Amino acid sequence: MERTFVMIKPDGVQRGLIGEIISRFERKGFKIVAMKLMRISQELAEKHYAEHREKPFFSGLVDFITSGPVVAMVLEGKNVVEVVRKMIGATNPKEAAPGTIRGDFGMSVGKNVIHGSDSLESAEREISLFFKDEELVEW
Amino acid sequence: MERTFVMIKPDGVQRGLIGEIISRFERKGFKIVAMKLMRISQELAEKHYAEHREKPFFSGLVDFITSGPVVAMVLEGKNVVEVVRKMIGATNPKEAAPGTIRGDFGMSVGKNVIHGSDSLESAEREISLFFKDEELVEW
Amino acid sequence: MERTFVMIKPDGVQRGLIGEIISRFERKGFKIVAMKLMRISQELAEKHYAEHREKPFFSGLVDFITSGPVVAMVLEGKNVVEVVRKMIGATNPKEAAPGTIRGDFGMSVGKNVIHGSDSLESAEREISLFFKDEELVEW
Amino acid sequence: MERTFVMIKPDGVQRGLIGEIISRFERKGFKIVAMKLMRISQELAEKHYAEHREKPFFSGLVDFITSGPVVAMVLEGKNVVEVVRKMIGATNPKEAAPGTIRGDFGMSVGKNVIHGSDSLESAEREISLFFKDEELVEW
Amino acid sequence: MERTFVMIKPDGVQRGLIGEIISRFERKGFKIVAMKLMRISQELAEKHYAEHREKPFFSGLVDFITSGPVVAMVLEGKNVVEVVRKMIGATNPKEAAPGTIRGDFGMSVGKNVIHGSDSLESAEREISLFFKDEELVEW
Amino acid sequence: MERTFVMIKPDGVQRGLIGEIISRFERKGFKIVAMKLMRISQELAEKHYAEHREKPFFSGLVDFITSGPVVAMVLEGKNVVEVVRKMIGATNPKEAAPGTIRGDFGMSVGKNVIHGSDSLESAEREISLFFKDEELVEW
């Protein structure tokens, strides 16, 4: 059954938006099957953002995801990857539709509160990267 | 500084109240310094409820608490143990005041949505039981 | 099992509080087993308020209660009568506790947004008065 | 003055979404002029869904609207038919815009929480089908 | 740093929507740097709506913004003019996207709850018109 | 008729709680008859807190209250002073009941989010201190 990775970023955590974000996913009927508050190491951040490593300001992108506690989480349900992407909305919070997490809360592209996997492929990669098998919980 | 332990129980998880509960702690200004979704083992459930092990409802407690995922968490702030207990309210949701978590959501004395340490000592025992030091996160 | 009667009064209806009120009962885990929007007749209003028919505010009660649509409802669950009364709070919203329906929304002793049966007997009388058996719905 | 028919489906009712849905319509300024909790008979369901009778899985569509209590309701206000359609959003909750009832709550096309009339024509037909004249209330 | 003018119109004020509107802007991370409850004079209304003076029903447009207290306010933050325009949504509340203030609350074009500046140019004009320099507050 | 004074303090402003606070007063049915964002001057802060000027925390009070913008407001309605005090709750948020403003949001006795007049006399003094007559708005 389909799963996606979500990270509540340090700005989401620091601004007290964790409950609000989770409620949106629970109201929508998804299952949290893994979740933890953590601090992301340098290495892990670079691995996570590997496809961005030759892009402008890579290190400001990394610096920021290591600048505070995040909530790492795996959601399960039908069309979860795609549905979570639409609930989160466009990377740029000015362009993200109203009613999306980024349209309603995000302050800028760099401070856009939350990440969700792009694709089936990147969900599987991000889930394996952040969680061991034993951290997944059945329900 | 002062820390308390909170558990969103399987009824709170299964009913989609994780976010709402977390939001009350965030709006209150507390800092989540550790958090995880988990399944509680038989042994962990018995150590946690050790004081009630001679009571005739002990199997009802244990079977319930290990029946689905819970969210375990550590909260930090001034008077956190006392303040969190007041926010959660009386064990029996029928007696819990309106505006408490148990008063607004609990459905029975056993299905009361959430637990919070009841003293300084209980908070130290419970945090030690549920978390290793490495799962604690400085902001 | 145990049932109580609830009426969202014409002020609650006219101010747009039906959903909010219903949501508190749903988040609390009660089952709505009968519900309807209605206009209360003169006769129904007098039978309902029969005990106050010698009081000098009786015309104020009756004219108010039959002045716009109400929502009549039957709620079911453990301790529902007592729990619903506590959720609704004291008759005079000035005395009702914060977090109650009357404490959060009521504007005067007469415009107090909502009624809930005050005992087992009162709940049986009121349900009988407002609903025929065929309007009861098993889940 | 324009009216539309809304049905909160059994999944909306069973998941405790009745207040939330009603609040969205009351915040938007519409009047509930009829409402009831009911169970839909086989006959009524088939009549309601008559235009679908030669389409795939008709009977799964019927089976489901009879599988639990629904809330039947008539809303009144300007552009109500069309405005309610946009508030409810696309039949498919994956495609329904964020901020719509189906985008925020719906789990699938079959479990999409709510129905609202398509057209002036089908509102008039659905209202007559579910309500007698005396169940409409003036305000 | 960019600023925009917002007016909560008399219908928004009269329907108790002031907190809700402000919360949407605070959740989005904007700063209120000026705000007041006031009554708009005839002169000020005509000046405010000067570009509409040769359009149909100008005086009904004016009559209405003078028919009750409004909240005048200046918001500051990045892309504030444009982001506030999208949060408020299309002038016509039937066409305004769900999740926008006008899509969720507005009853009609004339009763559309709220105004926000069109452009950098009209923000500067509307701010100067409603506020003296000393009413702006630094933070 | 009866009026009280309310101040959303700099913690309430800086944390993004203005709307939420205002919404509780609006849902309660009170009329805002004057309101403004302001910076409080040293002198205004000392006159307001005159009774505490010999207490060792007086500098902590004054420095805090003049440390960022506040929202000053006048609310009108039956029993407004008493009712608003109950809604706000006890000075020390640890003692304030759940469902109060201070109980749900206050983080310390000094950072308690909000002030409301404590008597009829105090309300007259405070309204006089913070507002000129011309800032009062009849609905």
Image (cartoon, coloured by chain):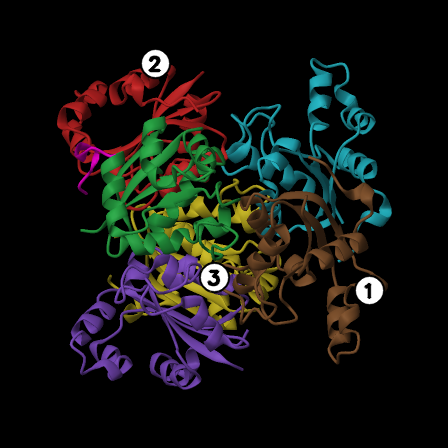
Chain colours: A cyan, B brown, C purple, D yellow, E red, F green
Q: Are marks 2 and 1 on the same chain?
A: no
Q: Is residue B125 above or below residue B77?
A: below
Q: Nearer the viewer, residue C60 or B25?
A: B25
Position of residue C50 in the picture relative to residue B29 (left or right): left
Give the residue type that dot 3 points to: Arg
CA gap between label 2 and label 1 equals 67 Å
Q: Residue at x 17, y 37 (%)?
A: E67
Position of residue C36 in the picture relative to residue A8 (left or right): left
Q: Are marks 1 and 3 on the same chain?
A: no
Q: Nearer the viewer, mark 1 or mark 3?
A: 1
Q: Residue at x 76, y 42 (%)?
A: B136
Q: Chain of mark 3?
A: C
Asked if the residue under mark 1 is in contact with the one under mark 2, i.e. CB atoms within 8 Å, the reply is no
Using a 10 Å C-alpha cutoff, classify the residue at mark 2 as few (fewer than 14 neighbours), some (14 to 19) or many (20 or more): few
Q: Chain of mark 1?
A: B
Give the residue type that dot 2 points to: Glu
Q: Is residue F120 visible?
A: yes
Q: Is residue F133 magenta?
A: yes
Q: Which residue is mark 1?
A: B47
Q: Position of residue C17 (x, y in %)?
A: 37, 57
Give the residue type that dot 1 points to: Lys
Q: Nearer the viewer, mark 3 or mark 2?
A: 3
Residue numbers of the magenta segment: F131-139
Residue E124 badge: none
Q: Position of residue B48 (x, y in %)?
A: 78, 63
Q: Which residue is mark 2?
A: E121
Q: Which residue is mark 3?
A: C24
Q: Residue at x 19, y 35 (%)?
A: E64
